[PDB]
Image (cartoon, coloured by chain):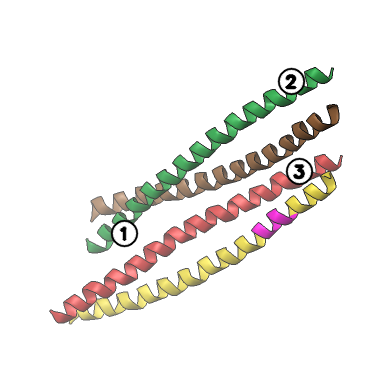
Chain colours: A green, B red, C brown, D yellow
């Protein structure tokens, strides 16, 4: 009982940590996606100005 | 052509790197399990020696 | 014991899948890093060249 | 520029690969060490339990 209890306890702790890491990856993908939208608009517009 | 070869090698090499990083976190899970196990078995082994 | 065993197995599967997902997110965010740098070079060098 | 950029990318990612190989090797090494400590301690646990 003690064996599996402590094992499950630390494992649950790490599942929480994994959720946090998942969260920061989601945030960074949001940031990079916004930036790629902005720079996409910039490059398309500069090509239009070229033409 | 060179950019096409670059792309091929880039995503293949990225694939192997995420395989490696997955193994990192996963073997590191088993490591924390093992180390906590060893610690707490030490713990109650001492206690039950006192008993 | 049966309850703890089921919980431990489920959470071990969870943390393995979490490791895999975190790995592939790391891969894709590195890819986004690369694409960002590449097309930033594109659009900025294009500002200079067109000007 | 593309030659140099792709070459350095392959450098960075390959470096990640062998470093990660070293790290994984470390994972299995200390993992077996820890699980050996756990196994021997568990044997002694069985002995003291019987006594």
Residue, disc 1? A7
Disc 1 on helix, strand or loop?
helix
Residue at left offset 52%, top offset 58%: B24
Residue, disc 2? A45
Q: In the rendered structure, does residue D12 fall within the stretch colored magenta?
A: yes
The image shows residue C29, relative to residue D45, as above or below, that is above
Where's the N terminus of chain B, which quadrant? top right
Report whether B17 appears left or right of C23.
right
Q: CA distance from mark 2 to mark 1?
A: 57 Å
Do the residues at pointers 3 and 2 share their chain? no
Residue A8: x percent and y percent? 30, 55
Residue, disc 3? B8
Residue B5: x percent and y percent? 81, 44
Which residue occupies the extreme left position in the image? B51
Q: CA distance from mark 3 to mark 1?
A: 42 Å
Q: Main secondary structure of the magenta part?
A: helix
Disc 3 on helix, strand or loop?
helix
Report whether C14 appears left or right of D11.
left
Q: Mark 1 and mark 2 in contact (Cβ < 8 Å)?
A: no
């Amino acid at each position: 009982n003690a064996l599996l209890g402590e094992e499950a306890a630390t494992l649950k702790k790490r599942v929480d940590q994994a959720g946090l890491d998942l969260a920061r990856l989601s945030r960074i993908e949001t940031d990079l996606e916004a930036q790629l939208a902005a720079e996409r608009a910039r490059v398309q517009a500069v090509e239009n100005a070229l033409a | 052509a060179h950019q096409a070869d670059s792309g091929r090698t880039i995503r293949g090499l990225e694939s192997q790197v995420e395989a490696n990083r997955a193994e990192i976190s996963a073997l590191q899970t088993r490591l924390e399990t093992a180390t906590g196990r060893a610690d707490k078995l030490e713990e109650m082994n001492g206690q039950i020696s006192a008993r």
